[PDB]
Length: 94
Image 1 (tube, rainbow, N blue to C red):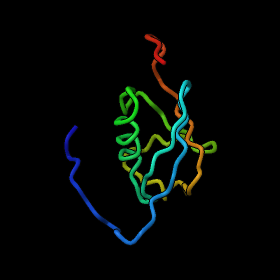
Image 2 (spheres, helix red, strand yellow; image 1 turned 90 degrees about the horizontal axis):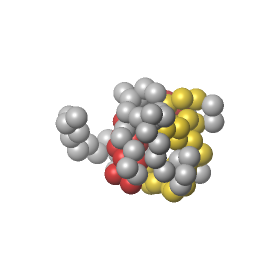
Image 3 (cartoon, rainbow, N blue to C red; image 1 turned 180 degrees about the vertical axis):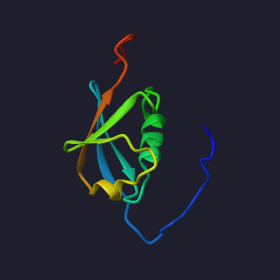
Image 4 (cartoon, helix red, strand yellow; image 1 turned 45 degrees about the vertical axis):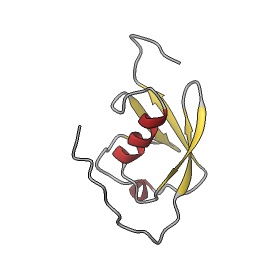
């Protein structure tokens, strides 16, 4: 909620293509390799209806629950399969 300032840590870098898999839809997003987990969910939140805190990102067995860490911390490269498990079972959604 706020605090989202613009920052260009590296302009001379190629953004990677991550595969965002929901329990319904599948789409690819261009994100930086030093992108924060929060900033990953930010971009996904812009695409999908799911709120950031409710959707959990799973990368090849690792739960990306640390909002403060970056993707490089988990070792995420291009064509990665990010499985998004939605933690909302009281009211279902597509």
